[PDB]
Image (cartoon, coloured by chain):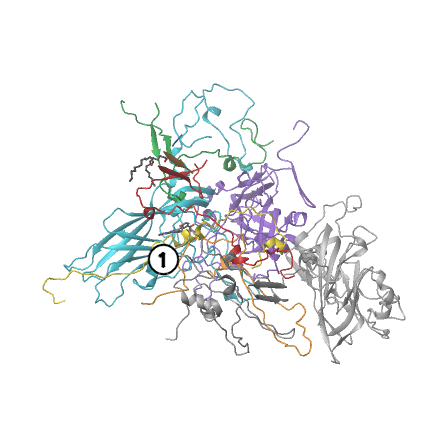
Chain colours: A purple, D orange, E brown, F blue, G red, H green, I cyan, J yellow
Amino acid sequence: EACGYSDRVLQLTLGNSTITTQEAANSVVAYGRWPEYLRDSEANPVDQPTEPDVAACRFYTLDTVSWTKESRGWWWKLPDALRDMGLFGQNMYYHYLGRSGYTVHVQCNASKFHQGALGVFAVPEMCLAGDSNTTTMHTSYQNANPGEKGGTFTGTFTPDNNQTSPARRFCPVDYLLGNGTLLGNAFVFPHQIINLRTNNCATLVLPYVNSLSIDSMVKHNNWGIAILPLAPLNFASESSPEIPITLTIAPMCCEFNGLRNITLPRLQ
Amino acid sequence: EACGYSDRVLQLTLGNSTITTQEAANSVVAYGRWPEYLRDSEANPVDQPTEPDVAACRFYTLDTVSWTKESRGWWWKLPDALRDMGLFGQNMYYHYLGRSGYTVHVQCNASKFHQGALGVFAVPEMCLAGDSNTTTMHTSYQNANPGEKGGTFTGTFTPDNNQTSPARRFCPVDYLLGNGTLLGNAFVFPHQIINLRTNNCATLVLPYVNSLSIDSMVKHNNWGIAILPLAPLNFASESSPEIPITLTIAPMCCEFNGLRNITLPRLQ
Amino acid sequence: EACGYSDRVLQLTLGNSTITTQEAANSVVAYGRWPEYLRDSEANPVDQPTEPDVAACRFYTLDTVSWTKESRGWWWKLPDALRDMGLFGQNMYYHYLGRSGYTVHVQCNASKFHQGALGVFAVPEMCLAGDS
Amino acid sequence: IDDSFTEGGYISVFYQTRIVVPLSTPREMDILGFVSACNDFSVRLLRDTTHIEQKA
Amino acid sequence: GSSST
Amino acid sequence: GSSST
Amino acid sequence: GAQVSSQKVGAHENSSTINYTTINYYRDSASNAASKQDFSQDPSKFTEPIKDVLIKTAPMLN
Amino acid sequence: GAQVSSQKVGAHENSSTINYTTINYYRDSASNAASKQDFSQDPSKFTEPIKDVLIKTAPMLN
Amino acid sequence: AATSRDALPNTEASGPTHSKEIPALTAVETGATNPLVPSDTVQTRHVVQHRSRSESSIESFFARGACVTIMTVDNPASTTNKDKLFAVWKITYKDTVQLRRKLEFFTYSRFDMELTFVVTANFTETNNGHALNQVYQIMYVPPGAPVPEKWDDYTWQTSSNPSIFYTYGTAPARISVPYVGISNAYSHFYDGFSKVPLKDQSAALGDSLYGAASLNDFGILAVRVVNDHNPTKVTSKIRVYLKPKHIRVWCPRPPRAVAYYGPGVDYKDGTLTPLSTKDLTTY
Amino acid sequence: TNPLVPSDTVQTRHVVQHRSRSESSIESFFARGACVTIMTVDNPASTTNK
Ligand SMILES: CCOC(=O)c1ccc(OCCC2CCN(c3ccc(C)nn3)CC2)cc1
Ligand SMILES: *C(=O)CCCCCCCCCCCCC
Ligand SMILES: *C(=O)CCCCCCCCCCCCC
């Protein structure tokens, strides 16, 4: 705008939380769909839903990770990364059913003398490959669901040889997007690129996507967030630079059905 | 009604919970006021409220107590008795402020050959007397707030003599309503009587009452439920009869303000 | 009804017989169909029918049985249970063909201190299993 | 069939207070339970039952 | 002709 | 009859 | 004599009622296929066979 | 109930629209052939999923 | 209103430019692809376009019967000590790789299905006897229904299960199936489990496979030769072809780049390097 | 049988129902060819004694 408004400068407000950014590269709305509540024509559980509004639909900041020249990539699953986040988590665990959309805001700033580009991908149904060559589909629920902590990509497939006490975890090779497909094509998924000369952040608005109108949030993740270094971090002449990446996520239009006693999962 | 409807037969439904009663003695609405949400003209915190609706405003059943010929009486405080009840409790502890109304349904059935009458009183601001004659206003938060478990009335004032390690608890003498006033006048408070020849229950609908539109639910109880045997339990010729009293309470029109991290109280 | 009528208190009258009940739980009409005489459109034997009316369509009381803690259950077949009942039986045995509907009233009273529940079932074509 | 992916949940019954009788009255009694479908209930994909069979 | 439905 | 297109 | 009726279309193509046509070739009704154009009825004669109509909000016994 | 539709005629004879006819014989839609009369959509939800509409002649970032 | 077989846009004539409009310069960080046509960066003539995207429509891409399995059955001599082999197949598109890869370009799908059955038979022994023409029974057993244990047990009665009786030598058998899913669309991928491990409950009880939803998703096809045992043994194979008709698909995915290893997204060591050597400055 | 729906005993939302009882109609329940018998016949050599 003529009196100063810009595509790089955004303010987002949800509940009692506000995010400001002075160096954005617009925002992505996945598949052109803004989040919405479940319509009566697509509804299925007949009981009155719980809709927590401002208490759950607000910005939760997860633990900050660190980007270095050794960094192969990081991944998170939704709703899993938010499972212990305030009243969103409580509402999630007290109900059999739940659905939610999300605003994902990835934060990474550096300086006009740094280089590097992060691919921020939102994958619907991000099924990842496990660590075994003798058995298939065997990653334990505990290993499959890291919570806020997330997981990482590796540059090398290294098979779990302990047949008597199997590790039962994923082994996500980065150029294969951890799922057997080439990373260069991951751009057909909703994404943004944090290229350090251009922007400090990525912002993706994600609708609820599923083959069902509502589902078990505890048994099933709808979206996976994959962040990979498309171009490695570099600074001045320092052989070992580091810059933080902070992930902040807000649930949107979340509703819950089937209230009963709280689910206490075996997470270890 | 001509095709069978009656004042004794009620069905109450809130959220996913339904109560039936075939032997009621109508219902009381305290001070003629049904619960309501806070109006804009009486509002005070400016932030968007959290209103949990069906997830919190449903019937919670507390631990069943037992009525015997030795029973002097029982008391509970609201919101305290419901502090660990599902998503009502979570919403209570995550917010600085909260207000709520209640439907209290006291349950006590026996048989056409038993006798006894329970006075069920709802007292606004039910401040009780402590156990000390050397210091005043000194009942600890822990002793003042028994949670679901409630407290009991005694027929005798017995002063805490341990001056070096004071018990710091209440000593509610029954004919003085635990507060220095005579029980016979407690009928100016909203009440019902469970007289075993007439009814199996008492039902009281309580508005939010306070000198403020909204307050700290953790620091302050708005209502006290006092149940006392006006006429002692008696059965056939048994010298030691017993019948259960079950207390079921539902929050109504509850809203919360000032969201932040969860309060973890020192309750021991 | 406002001036006292109730679902528990019934009076049934057929012919010269009347039944009163002060503790009923409504009445069942099987498959929603009240008994009726055979219509000309569904008729088959061409001869003028015999219709005994009040002489046969009245209440016959069968022998009283006794319920105990050993009791496994009782059964009857219709028209067979009524075969020796007054002019219904005579009319039944003098004709090759016959059709009839029925009002069945099972009676069992006890006291406010007894317990027990009897399932009273009316089965169309109740073929039973033999002993071999 | 029993399947965790399409599991329905749990029915349970409890005493809210207790059964109370007078003297000269039986202290034990039975309850009977009945199940039926609501008007919004439907079924699909016709198949053979395991509740009848014919060995030989 | 055609009986429609 | 004939639905044309 | 061609009979034209509507299909209840479930999964649609990325492609308005769809119809199908039927002609009976034989004189005897027994030879005909099943129409499947069937009617539903209310369960009352089995579920509520009582003489006095029940009101679900009122006491069943009065 | 006969459905009549146009062919997209590629190689013509040395010989005006050409049509083809279709009749559905079965009551269930699943039994039907594929129409191939399909619709196209614009790729925007995949190619341009950004919140602020882009003008290709203007700077993408401003 | 744009049909798949409509012609693509005409190229418009475009002349020289000296302007402040910058179509060539962009920023892919935004998540968008730059919508450029040749007349944005070069001078173009007018072309009247005739080409169409008709054959790359989702229907057209999938409108082909693909082999999803080969079932083996036989009919031995009465005297043999081995049982007469009838076939049981757990129905899926994942036992072969080609159609699976095409469907996996998408996360979700709805389709009606056409199943076509090609049946071939042959003699096994250097014997010289004969077999009269075989009739085959292909019975669908949906989850819950009694699975056959013997080629001739009561289950083959099919009072309620759908069965096809195929005569050898006639045109290949064919049936259509509606969209049978208990979801609003078939999930090609399921990032989840069918059970929740509960703290209070033992590890063994809470365990389930990653990515697997209903243990018996859609039942099985059971096939047998209805003919009685013949002195000369004949072995037969039933090839099943699946065609997704009246199909709709959602959420695009990159294609499988490395060899399939089982029903899930798992990859095996040694099959992970698909790309060939080619130098940066070599055409 | 008590004609109750969920909104009689619990709080319910509005759902637009799409399911049908089409396949449990009496026709649909029986519209399948079922095996009722297996008959055995033969054609022997002229010379056999059976
Ligand atoms: C989750 C992975 O697999 C699938 O999504 C997927 C796999 C198979 C698909 O087919 C649906 C299942 C069945 C449906 C019924 N069916 C029948 C039915 C009748 C007969 C005689 N023969 N086969 C055969 C296939 C449809 C989807
Ligand atoms: C009504 O049926 C008039 C139109 C008939 C159109 C031709 C029908 C196809 C041939 C059927 C031949 C007769 C079958 C016994
Ligand atoms: C609309 O279809 C009316 C005209 C029908 C013309 C005859 C169709 C050819 C015979 C089809 C017979 C029915 C197939 C189940």
Q: Which residue is mark 1?
A: I159
* Pick the front one: I174 or I44: I174
**Depicted C117 relative to depicted G47: above or below:** below
Q: Nearer the viewer, residue I100 or C69?
A: C69
Q: Amino acid at mark 1?
A: Ser
Q: Percent x, y for residue A4?
A: 67, 30
Mark 1 CB within 8 Å of ligand 1: no
Does residue A60 appear in this view? yes
Q: Position of residue I2 (x, y in %)?
A: 45, 30
Residue I166 lies, with reference to residue A111, above or below; the image says below
Q: Where in the figure is residue A88, as x and y percent of width and height?
A: 63, 52
Left or right for A63, reference J42 = right
- Placement of C125 over or under E3, stated as above or below: below
Label 1 residue SS? loop
Residue A247 seen in the current view: no
Q: Residue furthest left?
A: J47
Chain holding disc 1: I
